Amino acid sequence: MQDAFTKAIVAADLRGSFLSEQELNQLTNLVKESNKRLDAVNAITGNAAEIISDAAHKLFAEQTDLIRPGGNAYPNRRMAACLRDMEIILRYVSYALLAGDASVLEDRCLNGLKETYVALGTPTRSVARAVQLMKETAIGYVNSPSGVTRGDCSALVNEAATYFDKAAASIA
Amino acid sequence: MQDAFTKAIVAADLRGSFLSEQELNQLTNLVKESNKRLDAVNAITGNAAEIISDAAHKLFAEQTDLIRPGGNAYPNRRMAACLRDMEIILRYVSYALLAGDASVLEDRCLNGLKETYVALGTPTRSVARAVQLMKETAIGYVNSPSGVTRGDCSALVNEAATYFDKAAASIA
Amino acid sequence: MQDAFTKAIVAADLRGSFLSEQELNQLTNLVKESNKRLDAVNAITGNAAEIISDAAHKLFAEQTDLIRPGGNAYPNRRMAACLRDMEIILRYVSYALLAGDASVLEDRCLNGLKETYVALGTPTRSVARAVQLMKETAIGYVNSPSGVTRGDCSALVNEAATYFDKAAASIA
Amino acid sequence: MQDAFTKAIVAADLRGSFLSEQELNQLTNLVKESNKRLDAVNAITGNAAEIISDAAHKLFAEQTDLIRPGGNAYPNRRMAACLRDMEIILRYVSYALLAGDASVLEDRCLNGLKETYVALGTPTRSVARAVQLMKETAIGYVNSPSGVTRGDCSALVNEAATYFDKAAASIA
Amino acid sequence: YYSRPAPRATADGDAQTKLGITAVAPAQAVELRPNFGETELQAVIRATYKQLFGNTYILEADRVVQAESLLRNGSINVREFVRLLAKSELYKERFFHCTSNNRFIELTFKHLLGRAPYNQSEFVEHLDRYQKSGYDAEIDSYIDSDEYRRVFGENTVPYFRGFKYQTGQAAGVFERTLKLYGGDADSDTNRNRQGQLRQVDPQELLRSGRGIV
Amino acid sequence: MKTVITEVIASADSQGRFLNNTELQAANGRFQRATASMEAARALTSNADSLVKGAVQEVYNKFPYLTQPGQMGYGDTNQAKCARDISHYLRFITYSLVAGGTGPLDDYIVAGLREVNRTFNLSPSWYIEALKHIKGKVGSQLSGQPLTEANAYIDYCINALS
Amino acid sequence: MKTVITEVIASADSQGRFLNNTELQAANGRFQRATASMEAARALTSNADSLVKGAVQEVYNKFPYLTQPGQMGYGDTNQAKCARDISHYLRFITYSLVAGGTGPLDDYIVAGLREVNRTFNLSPSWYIEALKHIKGKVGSQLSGQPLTEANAYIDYCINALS
Amino acid sequence: MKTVITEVIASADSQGRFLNNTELQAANGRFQRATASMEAARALTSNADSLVKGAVQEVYNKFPYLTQPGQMGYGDTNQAKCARDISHYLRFITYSLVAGGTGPLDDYIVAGLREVNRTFNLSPSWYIEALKHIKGKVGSQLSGQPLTEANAYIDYCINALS
Ligand SMILES: *[C@H](C)[C@H]1/C(=C/c2[nH]c(/C=C3N=C(/C=C4\NC(=O)C(CC)=C4C)C(C)=C\3CCC(=O)O)c(CCC(=O)O)c2C)NC(=O)[C@@H]1C
Ligand SMILES: *[C@H](C)[C@H]1/C(=C/c2[nH]c(/C=C3N=C(/C=C4\NC(=O)C(CC)=C4C)C(C)=C\3CCC(=O)O)c(CCC(=O)O)c2C)NC(=O)[C@@H]1C
Ligand SMILES: *[C@H](C)[C@H]1/C(=C/c2[nH]c(/C=C3N=C(/C=C4\NC(=O)C(CC)=C4C)C(C)=C\3CCC(=O)O)c(CCC(=O)O)c2C)NC(=O)[C@@H]1C
Ligand SMILES: *[C@H](C)[C@H]1/C(=C/c2[nH]c(/C=C3N=C(/C=C4\NC(=O)C(CC)=C4C)C(C)=C\3CCC(=O)O)c(CCC(=O)O)c2C)NC(=O)[C@@H]1C
Ligand SMILES: *[C@H](C)[C@H]1/C(=C/c2[nH]c(/C=C3N=C(/C=C4\NC(=O)C(CC)=C4C)C(C)=C\3CCC(=O)O)c(CCC(=O)O)c2C)NC(=O)[C@@H]1C
Ligand SMILES: *[C@H](C)[C@H]1/C(=C/c2[nH]c(/C=C3N=C(/C=C4\NC(=O)C(CC)=C4C)C(C)=C\3CCC(=O)O)c(CCC(=O)O)c2C)NC(=O)[C@@H]1C
Ligand SMILES: *[C@H](C)[C@H]1/C(=C/c2[nH]c(/C=C3N=C(/C=C4\NC(=O)C(CC)=C4C)C(C)=C\3CCC(=O)O)c(CCC(=O)O)c2C)NC(=O)[C@@H]1C
Ligand SMILES: *[C@H](C)[C@H]1/C(=C/c2[nH]c(/C=C3N=C(/C=C4\NC(=O)C(CC)=C4C)C(C)=C\3CCC(=O)O)c(CCC(=O)O)c2C)NC(=O)[C@@H]1C
Ligand SMILES: *[C@H](C)[C@H]1/C(=C/c2[nH]c(/C=C3N=C(/C=C4\NC(=O)C(CC)=C4C)C(C)=C\3CCC(=O)O)c(CCC(=O)O)c2C)NC(=O)[C@@H]1C
Ligand SMILES: *[C@H](C)[C@H]1/C(=C/c2[nH]c(/C=C3N=C(/C=C4\NC(=O)C(CC)=C4C)C(C)=C\3CCC(=O)O)c(CCC(=O)O)c2C)NC(=O)[C@@H]1C
Ligand SMILES: *[C@H](C)[C@H]1/C(=C/c2[nH]c(/C=C3N=C(/C=C4\NC(=O)C(CC)=C4C)C(C)=C\3CCC(=O)O)c(CCC(=O)O)c2C)NC(=O)[C@@H]1C
């Protein structure tokens, strides 16, 4: 696998060089944010169940047909599959967020996902939608926590977004 | 898997509806024929060995080259395979006949058979031929038994045919 | 598998015939050379380690980049694989040499190799080069042994070459 | 598996009770020593290779028969095993040391070791000896480092000993 | 007349050698026996490593010494040795963490049973299994399953069952496994350009039945 | 989908053998029974609606608080759903009778039941009552084997739900 | 049992390798955290009882009907049980804080949670409230990291329950 | 590549679960340590060259005969290589410090070490000295935790080599 640190290393390796001082300063800074980074993750994990639950409700309010006979989220088993999937995607996203790198997400999760969905007949569009719905709810928590020292998390928040979006895009 | 009953169900499900009274009457009558249906199957199974034996003889009388050195049914090992295959196809056909549905046959047996045969270099045409030869012999028994109450089996006989033919076609 | 004898058989079989007297005399003669044949093989096996060691040194002196960061033979892990590949190829070649037939080599060793090399990004040309480097060194031993009865091994030597070359070609 | 913390928990559980304040104070202080604890482990791991190498030399100087034909450490194959084993035991000891509990070492390695050795005909006595030889060398490092903050490690040192000894005993 | 070179005049072997499946087709089976010579042990070990890891190259450091010792004492059977290898950092790093679960399932299917996946349902039972319980429970379900026990049940190294007719096979294994095997020098490799990707296309699965769930 | 017919085929298929007398005997069983099964289905199909109303209703009596504001039973949307759901159960039990196996029930309803219900906080209990109430009504319109069949399937769900 | 320390050992053991720097770094993390964790535990342990009373209570307010006769909340036995259970949850949470991993929680509470709850018809919802109410109280006695830790674990259960 | 962060993800991933408190604790450890690690790297990176010269040199003192004609230490090419190699080892050691795991070392240096060395008849011994000599020098420019870290990694190789 890969993450922010390892990555920079690898790059450096092919040049054949010690790490540039400039490059260290990326990592040095990254460290400093750690605490923020962590809490972000913690927030997702803490609220996981909910995040999904929520997103689902909204997804089905919008696309009523998914839950109608002939739709893709019917019958029960399909609905369960759909829920399961949403969760998974989330799980990965979180992982990435900690790593500070998309990779884990791309390789385990996104890679081949679209085509799977296609073969099954799952409407990729809707999947993507769900991912976004999730995104918003998730940010909601990341950004509004309780008992945490107040400061600016934007930087992290945006990176979070990006991950969600890579997801949305590749699925779609 | 699937069969006549299950199928009708599934259809009904996508409409989202209870079964039509009309539709019940398909199944109701299907039941009535059961006994006939069964005997048909029984006849095949009872004569299995023979059916094949016979068909083979005829197949090789026609296409002498198969059994000539360098042909596809030579040497022994190949010949064995060829016999084995015939049997299998038969077996499935029977299955279908009982189910009252092609599916089982199409999915496990036929689907991708052609491609296999291609890759191996086995001549699909001959295979198809064999299937027909089988067909005729089989019907022979279905249609001319002993100790059964005399009546009309045509309906079943034709359906039998169709199964054989789907086979012939998809292989060919 | 296959080898010189078996092969001739197979040919004969497709004609459908007993072996030609002429054809026997090919095999009869082939037998006579056995002893030479054997010693040839023995020479390779005896010197194996070195053959490779040698070839490698030369390979890396020539293609400096392979061992540079970013090249294919760097780092250790990769280097190890490359040595190992060389051994495997050699091993097979020897096998062939004994069999008196390319087949074994083509099927087990060369078959699929190109595509692998492609996917990995390994530069096929260099691989081929290595194979040759090996060839020359190997012949070196085959052709200059000690304590063997003096005579002419050319016939064998050339066949050896061919094997190496089939290798070079199919890889390249 | 188990360790100091987990253990205390489990005990508490069967009483059905919250942890006694007294009991917390065991763990509280255990924490405080952590840093020392860690360095201890680090010292072993850092010197591993050596520890063994050393012990072996001494073992074989003493029990010359092991390495003579008919002995248990002869021939090469066996010798290799014997070295491997020593190492393993070491590894486990270290593990324990970190955990702050014997459990892991006994369950993973010691439980059944004696009997194995017996069945093979390995002289358990000698094995035990080796373990001690190791012990002494190991302590040597744990207790005499450079560039670590100077202080008292005794407490840890003794616990280390005990682990080694449990090993020695159960094997013997 | 009844003896004459047929006009096709393909050999017996021909059909296999043209595909490159000549070694795997009726593959040889390696069994460990009640008391084993030093060579039988080392054959079995080589065969396992080659089959589980998919002819990918295992260095001298990658080997797992303990599992091999236990296999030497007699304290674990070959079936247990297989589980230990399968449940291992090295396996997980090659065929699990870099690929997608769809890709992994088809790999493990091939590694632990020489066939490819028979139909789409096989992906459902193994993907849900993985979310419900670990990787580990999933891997077990393979070795634990009756098909693993029925063939190569104990003390036998797993061998490719693909490319030969097996009872209750689906059609279109043959072709599917040809996508997975791809020749004696090919090997599935975490570390090739464009990463680790499924060969089996998802539309051919549905071509074999697809029930609800 | 699990029906008598599919199963024997499956079993036959696995062993790699022709359908012999053993399996046909079994099949025969399914067909003989059908007449009763079919009858039961016609009866449920007809009274569907009425059964549904009665059930939904029941549930509310049984669990008054559901109809209070801020609860699940409250506000028409939910009531509509609640109706729908029970109708889905009703249509599928009928399917099973006709198919001559639990099959239809299993994959459509039983599969994933738990997790669905967990994630949306549907309490199994409710459904159960619905069913029970139904069972009671059915216990009038039907009789003899037809009845027996209806029960079997209805119960099968109770057990799955609980 | 999963704690930081046990895991790294496990991982080291599986590979068959000595504990190297990688793992120690991890360990260091745990034990550094402990100081906060430990504090939290002392706080919960002390107020245990009071938290429990408050919780049990809450549940009843939230679900009045439980206290009615013929229900689960009704009659002392049940109340006793209800108390017991909530206390058990708290005890595991305290244990986990000290152990420095979810381990204790997973093995006692979580594994088999569903089926237990199903067979005895315990509604997850209830427990949850209990927890939430707790969380709220804890949100006074604690602060900063100590608090954060307490939450994490409390939540972990909420998620498992739901 | 094995770093603290990658591992916990991996472990989380295997079990199929979200990162819970357990793993974060571990992560935290990695991050707090980094400050020391990073420092050490800056120090090695700067003095690289000087360390290398000194090492190469040392080796020759230790094994005079290498510099004699017909040996491996002899003729500039070889000396150049010898330099290169040690420099490569140093670069990986710096990489590891920063990555916070042995990962980089394992994959570049260690894996395949043996066979390479065997086939080219590089004697581990040599490398070792190089390292040791280095370790000694580093034992001046650094101090406290920064030092400790540097050692760990340097050693890790010694052990792998031997
Ligand atoms: C929910 C938002 C939508 C939905 C999903 C859905 N998915 C399937 C089936 C599968 N989905 C996957 C997903 C993955 N494979 C992976 O490896 C990963 C990452 C690890 C993911 C996320 C796979 C493997 C399958 C096939 C196996 C299975 O059936 O579970 C279905 C069922 C399709 C069917 O007809 O069987 C569905 C419904 N569908 C919707 O309608 C939502 C928009
Ligand atoms: C960001 C989304 C929101 C936010 C975060 C935030 N956190 C801190 C500081 C800390 N947070 C933690 C958290 C952790 N460190 C760990 O080791 C773990 C796992 C065991 C966690 C959960 C810690 C320890 C700190 C430092 C001490 C403290 O609590 O102050 C800050 C302050 C910045 C800084 O750390 O330098 C912030 C901003 N708070 C917000 O306002 C965002 C909504
Ligand atoms: C006989 C009528 C004709 C014939 C048959 C033939 N088949 C093979 C080899 C194979 N046949 C199969 C086929 C199947 N696999 C399946 O899954 C099914 C049912 C779904 C079948 C029917 C397979 C897999 C093989 C290859 C492996 C094996 O031997 O089991 C041969 C031999 C060719 C070869 O080189 O293997 C032959 C001859 N060909 C004829 O000449 C007849 C017209
Ligand atoms: C059709 C190809 C042939 C034929 C069939 C035929 N059968 C019946 C009646 C019955 N056949 C059976 C057979 C079975 N029932 C079972 O349960 C089983 C499995 C153990 C079998 C094998 C039975 C019991 C009956 C009923 C009694 C009877 O023997 O008649 C008929 C009569 C019409 C009907 O609908 O039952 C017929 C016509 N007759 C033909 O023309 C072919 C020879
Ligand atoms: C060395 C002369 C050149 C070189 C070779 C090279 N090969 C690999 C990697 C692989 N090579 C093979 C090939 C085989 N597997 C077999 O069984 C056989 C014989 C039947 C061969 C020849 C395979 C399968 C691999 C993958 C191994 C694995 O995944 O562990 C490499 C390494 C590339 C990589 O990134 O792994 C190299 C370097 N390449 C050169 O640069 C030399 C000129
Ligand atoms: C050819 C590359 C070089 C060469 C070979 C050569 N060998 C012989 C004769 C023999 N060599 C062997 C060797 C073996 N026979 C075996 O059974 C085995 C395996 C156990 C070996 C290794 C034997 C037995 C003979 C016969 C007696 C002998 O060695 O003299 C010849 C003589 C020709 C002949 O035997 O017909 C030759 C020429 N000699 C060279 O100089 C070539 C470079
Ligand atoms: C060395 C100090 C002494 C010695 C050792 C020795 N051991 C064996 C054989 C085995 N060693 C073990 C031990 C283990 N395997 C494990 O997995 C574990 C951890 C649970 C241990 C500690 C086992 C079980 C074997 C057999 C398996 C194998 O060979 O790998 C031998 C060889 C004897 C034989 O016939 O196998 C030896 C020499 N004996 C001495 O002479 C030393 C005093
Ligand atoms: C004991 C066997 C010998 C010894 C140990 C010792 N260590 C310290 C202090 C520290 N040791 C460490 C080491 C680590 N902390 C970690 O997180 C890790 C893994 C990444 C290690 C290896 C640390 C950080 C400290 C704190 C202060 C420092 O700068 O070292 C002491 C002092 C007492 C204390 O616990 O702080 C001692 C005594 N030193 C000896 O002389 C013993 C022979
Ligand atoms: C009736 C006893 C209670 C009630 C029901 C109710 N149901 C939902 C939501 C769903 N209902 C189902 C059930 C099914 N859908 C299926 O596909 C099948 C299998 C064929 C069944 C059994 C489903 C899946 C949902 C969830 C998603 C959806 O909207 O369909 C609700 C809404 C709850 C919510 O939105 O969170 C309700 C209220 N209503 C009542 O009054 C009773 C308490
Ligand atoms: C409290 C919110 C409600 C309540 C609960 C209640 N629980 C039971 C029975 C059980 N509860 C549990 C729970 C646990 N037992 C354990 O060992 C653990 C893990 C440490 C837990 C969480 C169990 C297992 C039971 C089953 C039998 C038993 O008593 O142990 C009941 C009795 C229900 C019955 O019919 O068995 C009740 C009522 N009590 C209330 O008043 C609230 C509604
Ligand atoms: C230095 C102590 C001694 C010395 C060294 C020396 N090395 C080689 C050849 C090689 N050295 C390496 C080492 C590495 N290259 C890598 O990519 C890695 C991993 C990052 C390492 C550790 C390698 C792989 C080679 C072989 C290929 C090559 O030419 O680079 C030699 C030459 C040996 C030969 O046979 O050509 C020498 C001499 N020289 C001295 O003076 C010391 C004795």
Image (cartoon, coloured by chain):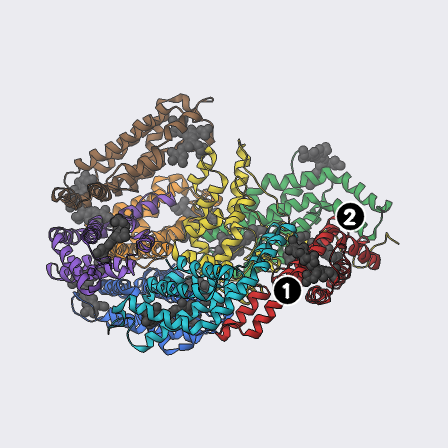
Chain colours: A blue, B red, C green, D brown, E yellow, F cyan, G purple, H orange
**Residue B152 visible in image:** yes
The image quadrant of residue H69 is top left
D69 lies above or below G24:
above
Question: How many residues crowd around disc 1 within 10 Å: few (fewer than 14), some, or many (20 or more)?
Answer: few
Residue that appears at 73% across and 65% down = B152
Q: Nearer the viewer, mark 2 or mark 1?
A: 1
**Badge count:** 2
Spot occupied by residue B169 in the image (x, y as percentages of width and height): 70, 67
Residue identified by numbered label 1: B32
- Secondary structure under badge 2? helix
G158 lies above or below D80:
below
- Secondary structure under badge 1? helix
The image quadrant of residue A25 is bottom left
Spot occupied by residue D112 in the image (x, y as percentages of width and height): 37, 31
Position of the C terminus of chain F, as image quadrant, is bottom left
Subunit of label 2: C
Pointer 2 with pointer 1, Cβ within 8 A: no
* Closer to the camera in the image, H125 or E158: E158
Spot occupied by residue C87 in the image (x, y as percentages of width and height): 56, 47
* Closer to the camera in the image, B60 or D66: B60
Which of the four quarters of the rendered structure image does ligand 7 lie in? Answer: top left
- From the viewer's perspective, tell me whether residue H64 is left or right of residue C78: left
Residue identified by numbered label 2: C8
Subunit of label 1: B
- Mark 2 and mark 1: span between their CA atoms? 65 Å
Tell me: is circle 1 under 8 Å from ligand 4.
yes
Amino acid type, callout 1 = Lys
**Label of residue G45 in the image:** none
